[PDB]
Amino acid sequence: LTNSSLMPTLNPMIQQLALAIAASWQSLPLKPYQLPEDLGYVEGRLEGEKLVIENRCYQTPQFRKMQLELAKVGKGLDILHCVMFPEPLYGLPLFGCDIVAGPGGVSAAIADLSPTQSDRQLPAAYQKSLAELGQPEFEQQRELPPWGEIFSEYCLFIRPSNVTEEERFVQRVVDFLQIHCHQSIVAEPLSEAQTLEHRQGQIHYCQQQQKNDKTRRVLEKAFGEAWAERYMSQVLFDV
Ligand SMILES: C=CC1=C(C)/C(=C/c2[nH]c(/C=C3N=C(/C=C4\NC(=O)C(C)=C4C=C)C(C)=C\3CCC(=O)O)c(CCC(=O)O)c2C)NC1=O
Ligand SMILES: [Cl-]
Ligand SMILES: [Cl-]
């Protein structure tokens, strides 16, 4: 991220989270994952503000696709997007987060380890480790939209009320990542039937994420409907 031209210009909480995700991934057995058209930097404008996106994407033997996206609309709107898609073979949940900020501060901060099992439960080891963290206190909880049924009971979705809350949220994401990295080492490869069940969970996650009109409208205002549909369905949430 020392290469990133966006990084210095993003909201501080976004910068801290980007750093924490990069630190988590840094020493993994990474290889690039080529996004469609080998996408890296992209920008677009139509009738309004310009949208700029830096797309980073990797894979490891355990993670089919690990994506970190940093974006800015004009000077008014900063976004961090991250998903780790695991190889269904290993039955790991989906780490994801999304942070949206403007000049007033962070408006939305979401993070989760989302289930892929048909029973919509996290694996037992994750349930146990996540419970041990204790329920965080946040002053300004937000209720997930209907498509958000995909998220676990541990999902965070807040407007951070102050710096203390910003730092508490980032630390909980660091904690989720530490659990996830550890559980990735200690799983326990699954049956062919179980592998299928997990693959299905991931497809469902992607289909539901594509119902988010908040993302879609930002993309559409800069690039148009067709571009946004391709980006959401082929670049971000590839089924
Ligand atoms: C890549 C480009 C990208 C854009 C343009 C983007 C925009 C974006 N996401 C938003 C919300 C949101 N974003 C998410 C969740 C996610 N979204 C995700 O991409 C992932 C991985 C999760 C969860 C792990 C949720 C649940 C909301 C709230 C939606 C709503 O209020 O309707 C919002 C509304 C913010 C607010 O209401 O304060 C915007 C503008 N997010 C992006 O990621
Ligand atoms: Cl909905
Ligand atoms: Cl508008």
Image (tube, grey):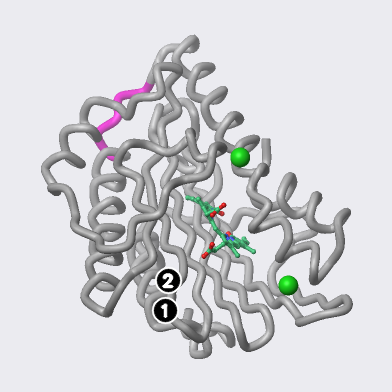
Is 104 displayed left or right of 210 in the figure?
left
Q: Amino acid at mark 2?
A: Ala
Count every numbered label the image shows and give the total. Answer: 2
Q: Nearer the viewer, residue 157 or 236?
A: 157
Q: Which residue is mark 1?
A: 15
Residue stretch rendered in magenta on the structure: 185-189
Looking at the rendered structure, which numbered label has been put on residue 18? 2
Q: Ligand 1 within 8 A of label 1's CB? A: no
Is 122 displayed left or right of 63 in the figure?
left
Indicate which quadrant contains ligand 2.
top right
Q: Nearer the viewer, residue 102 or 68?
A: 102
Q: Is residue 208 above or below residue 134?
A: above
Residue 157, x across and y down, in percent: 39, 54
Circle 1 sits in a helix, a strand or a loop, which is it? helix
Q: Nearer the viewer, residue 171 or 40?
A: 171
Please rate how many residues cluster around mark 2, counting C-alpha atoms within 10 Å: few if below 14, some from 14 to 19, many from 20: many
**To which quarter of the image does residue 129 belong?**
top left
Q: Amino acid at mark 1?
A: Gln
Q: Quadrant of the C terminus?
A: top right
Residue 49, x across and y down, in percent: 76, 82
Is 71 displayed left or right of 120 in the figure?
right
Residue visible at 49% across and 90% down in the picture: 8
Residue 187, x across and y down, in percent: 29, 30
Disc 2 + disc 1, Cβ < 8 Å: yes
